Length: 416
Image 1 (cartoon, rainbow, N blue to C red):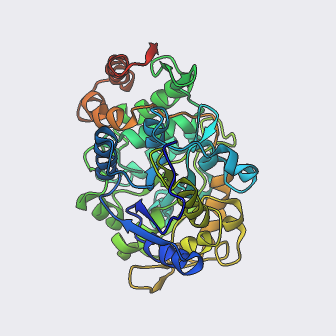
Image 2 (cartoon, rainbow, N blue to C red):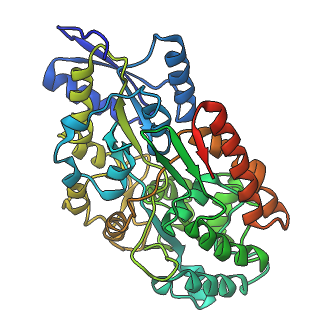
């Protein structure tokens, strides 16, 4: 570490999570320390800022919000403070997915602040009309059979949409127990085995059947207006996505309130297994001259009294206790952006399912040291599998080739 200020009066924090403004103010009231919190951009926008500040050797914050998939990019280059010694016993505090996701090469480099265990959200009105019981979709085969019944409703009806999304693909291979990205040798060696990984191949085989039999909406782009439209008019009947989705449903698909339900993700063989999609953490920059004060802040937000405030504003929790809290587990409504409670899931205690989804997450999935690059070019190689007849496996092989070449150029010892 560099030299450390003795009398710390303020710290600098970069984060786009809007709820952190009030949590920071609460922290200032408690400790007398000023928190200069700036939203310098959302995810990759902020990461570009971090990259430049690291390049330039100045201007970096003391703390930064970083999504789990992007942490290795900074941890492996030594740009994040190793906080392992300050987190003894935290393994019992955090849910398995988030806790696994803040560790790189056996060391903790951030604290979880929100999570996104995957869940199966479905339009019960459409499923019932198709003759599908959404509470009995336990295996990927069940989902395939449901997909045929839903599409039987009409040529414009689809169990879900997928036009090619790197995060979705990665999350589904995670769920299948895939480990196509493995970093070894203290961060120097990277094995990319997308083509040979058994989990990856299992998802490819399953998703390829839906693609080949024309059972997926492959044209609607995620988060587009046609996407929310499809969800509200029934042509997109369900979503395989993270536990944070309910907040977006209530505000962006208000017409369908009461028609949807949530269930656990179907798994290849019905085994207990799940993945995460999205979610973020707070990390201390290795360059910080205020390391201890920076850690104290993220400890309050991620581990102390800031956690309850965060959950109460609508963040999906990353810790075990919040999942069982009586102000969380018994929810049957979601507050919209105006504060109005909406019964979006028809009375279901949706957080009980999402709590179980958290417990099921597998803990052996690893991210690349260059996920931002990898996910940005995913569409360059897999797009043809959605606009055309390219087998997913063929696109994934080309993707792997580009990632291995990029890895070598960055200094890693690549294995195939």
